[PDB]
Amino acid sequence: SGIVQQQNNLLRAIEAQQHLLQLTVWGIKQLQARILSGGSGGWMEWDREINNYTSLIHSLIEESQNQQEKNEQELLGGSGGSGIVQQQNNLLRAIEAQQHLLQLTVWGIKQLQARILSGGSGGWMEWDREINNYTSLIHSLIEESQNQQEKNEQELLGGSGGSGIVQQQNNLLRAIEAQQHLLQLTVWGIKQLQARIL
């Protein structure tokens, strides 16, 4: 589909990730309250960062929804302008904020696992390697997307037949796909902890 529809799809995917992310945050808090005070070992810092990034991602979603509506109206009118490149900026910032949240949830799961399970049995050793692999992939994808965003905001041909906007859309799609997998990995880890604690 056209770039504006692809951006709609990606925004919807970010919203869906956010719902599940939020469930994971609450799941971790539920587990933590059973087994830890929450007043040592980084947990108050964690609560703060989670709170901030949750606010930030919702604000980014709002900004992206406003731009998406504008872009869809302009498309139906046969215009279109710098709104597509701005929307890639918006979606990249949302992806970055969700990556912070994902990494915070990984930290929380690791603290709980270290407390209430031992070592690498039960699938945990390979979980750790895959978390590190997918986190690695995502950081690479984000950096490339940041570099492409700068290129698109400086170059002249993005809306005149150049490749930069199509390239960037693929970068953002691959980033979200990797983050979908990372979230499935954190869900697995939470479920293992629930089986032990709840």
Image (tube, rainbow, N blue to C red):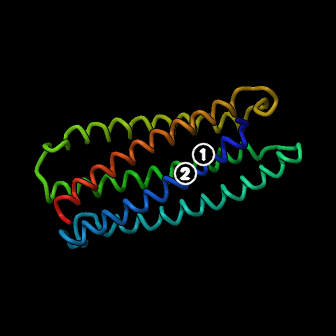
* Crowdedness near tag 1: few (<14), some (14–19) or many (≥20) residues, C-alpha within 10 Å: some
Q: Cα distance, mark 1 to mark 2?
A: 6 Å
Horizontal placement of 183 versus 57: left or right? Answer: left
Question: Does residue 108 appear left or right of residue 150 in this picture?
Answer: left
Is label 1 in a helix, a strand or a loop? helix
Q: Residue at x 22, y 53 (%)?
A: 192
Q: Residues within 10 Å of mark 2 (few under 14, many from 20)?
A: many
Q: Of helix, strand and loop, which one carries label 2?
A: helix
Residue ID at (41%, 64%): 50
Q: Quadrant of the N terminus?
A: top right
Query: What's the residue at 42%, 35% (across, down)?
Result: 137
State whether residue 104 is above or below residue 122.
below
The amino acid type of the residue labelled 1 equals Leu
Location of residue 155 by image quarter: top right
Looking at the image, is 168 positioned above or below residue 42? above
Residue type at the position of mark 2: Ile
* Residue 128 x, y percent position in the rendering: 25, 41
What residue occupies the far top of the structure in this picture? 162
Note whether 117 is above or below 34 in the view shown.
above
Residue 79: numbered disc: none
Reading the image, the residue beneath label 2 is 14
In the picture, residue 65 is in which quadrant? bottom right
Contact between marks 1 and 2 (CB within 8 A): the answer is yes
Quadrant of the rendering where the C terminus is positioned: bottom left
Describe residue 160's horizontal placement relative to residue 11 as left or right.
right
Give percent across and percent down for residue 171. 57, 34
Q: Is residue 116 left or right of residue 25?
A: left
Q: Give the x, y percent position of residue 82.
A: 78, 44
Kindly indicate the quadrant of the structure image that contains residue 75: top right
Where residue 183 sits in the image (x, y, percent)? Answer: 39, 48
Q: Residue at x 65, y 38 (%)?
A: 150
Identify the mark at residue 10; answer none if there is no mark.
Answer: 1
